[PDB]
Image (spheres, rainbow, N blue to C red):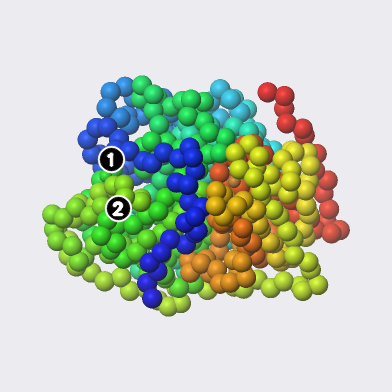
Amino acid sequence: SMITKYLYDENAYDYHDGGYRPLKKAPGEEHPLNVPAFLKPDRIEGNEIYYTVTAQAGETKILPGKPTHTWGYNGSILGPAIQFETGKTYHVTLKNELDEVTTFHWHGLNIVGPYEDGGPHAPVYPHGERKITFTVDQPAANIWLHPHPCPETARQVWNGLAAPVIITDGHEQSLKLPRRWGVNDFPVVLQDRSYHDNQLDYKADYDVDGTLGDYALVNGTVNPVVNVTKPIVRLRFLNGSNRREWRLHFADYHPFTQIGSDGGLLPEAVKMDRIMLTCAERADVLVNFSDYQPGQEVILQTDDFDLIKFKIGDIKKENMLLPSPLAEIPALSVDENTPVFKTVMSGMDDQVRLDGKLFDMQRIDTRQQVDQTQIWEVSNTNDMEGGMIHPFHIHGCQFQLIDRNGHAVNPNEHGWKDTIGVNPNETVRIKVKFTKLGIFMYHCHILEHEDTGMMAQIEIFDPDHPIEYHLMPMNHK
Ligand SMILES: [Cl-]
Ligand SMILES: [Cu+2]
Ligand SMILES: [Cu+2]
């Protein structure tokens, strides 16, 4: 009972779209996979860690010839790996060294909003700075940072801003996991881009239904290679693309083990020979290369396209061994006096809507009490023939899946999730408990759909501990 299918509906994959373009071989030689260094703290006082993160412009050598003008956090493209630990408090200085407004959103982080959350209510102006403070109150997980200024998010991510973020805790520490960063533990941020005289040009490539790129850009590198020197490797996959889905597998269908989802370690490790990710989903995977011989090249693909080359070195054979259960996920329970909240995604291209509306920065579409678990029922009304899979995301929480069209959820969806692909004609039920007060967004994570307005806000409140929010209209740009 290894999983041997992608877990979304094939009738609706990206490649059914009339504008779809498959990935092509990028020019130049093979390069070692870039692995970002961890961000060093500025100061440590008690359980209080100080970081600084700066959005900035630079030049990154990507393709043969001229370098590519890009944006990055603390560097020219992407960002450093940022480590958080459950129970610690962080003071993070957010500097904007670009010439337009950004925000710093910690996708997957349980943090109050709408200011610390770094969605569209939290502009950092050009040359400006904002400071946030927060305590991490969720288990170990792979999460990420990216910008969120409505309606410029898609372009900003295109231009290069995204960083991988790791939360660790004692449980994950207790496991015997590959942990030599850049040697047997890798971030794998999957993106796709097109270039024009080696440069980015979002406006040229824009599609309102989701912008696709011609080349595969992995951690900001084209034609990547990994030298395998220890056989058990952890790969922290993130779909960081604006729209493209990634259907990941080894060329020979060599099995691997999913150990984690968006919001953490899964309750049991899942053996599979392939996995599909929609926008913003994460899968934390172990691969054991021990059955290959030194000098072999093992190729990870998406669809039939060569994605990363693994060069097998002088490799002493080893075995994985994971406990069962892998982790304890506490079940949320709902009050059973509480109704089901229904939200409906509909349309494609510029006709996308969320409950028949487009986002309004001043409109609070829904409310829900802090610490109360509620069932949400998320629907996509696109046709089975011709529709698309919309990745649905909620800020400020991790949720659990109950069912997909009344049947069992996918086998890698029994833990904590924050982004969920919703297939055409499908109805998915989740359980959602908000643990922090504030205003949070929920939306499609196809960036162009988000920017069109396939997005809504929810106010999370404590009765007799109320607060009034002074939501502003969007600045006139
Ligand atoms: Cl390759
Ligand atoms: Cu988010
Ligand atoms: Cu969408």
Circle 1: residue type: Asn
Indicate yes or no: mark 1 CB to ligand 1 under 8 Å: yes
The residue that disc 2 covers is 300
Q: Secondary structure at mark 1?
A: loop
Q: Is residue 361 above or below residue 86?
A: above
Near mark 1 (Cα within 10 A), the count class, few <14, some 14-19 or many ≥20, is many
The mark that comes first in sequence, 1 or 2, is 1
Q: Quadrant of residue 257?
A: bottom left
Residue farthest to the front?
385
Of 142 and 14, the residue lying toward us? 14
Q: Residue at x 19, y 52 (%)?
A: 297
- Rendered image: mark on residue 223: 1
Give the quarter the ligand 1 occupies.
top left
Tell me the quadrant of the picture where the N terminus can be found. bottom left
- Rendered image: mark on residue 30: none
Circle 2: residue type: Leu
Q: Position of residue 94 (x, y in %)?
A: 57, 36
Of 344 and 149, the residue lying toward us? 344
Of 204 and 14, the residue lying toward us? 14
Q: Is residue 370 visible?
A: no
Q: Residue at x 40, y 69 (%)?
A: 3
Q: Is residue 99 visible?
A: yes
Q: Position of residue 51 (x, y in %)?
A: 51, 42
Q: Residue at x 28, y 63 (%)?
A: 254
Tell me the quadrant of the picture where the C terminus can be found. top right
Q: Secondary structure at mark 2?
A: strand
Q: Quadrant of residue 103?
A: top right
Q: Is residue 177 left or right of residue 116?
A: left
Q: Residue at x 56, y 30 (%)?
A: 96
Near mark 2 (Cα within 10 A), the count class, few <14, some 14-19 or many ≥20, is many
For the residues marked 1 and 2, what is the alpha-carbon distance in whole angstroms?
A: 12 Å
Residue farthest to the bottom?
324
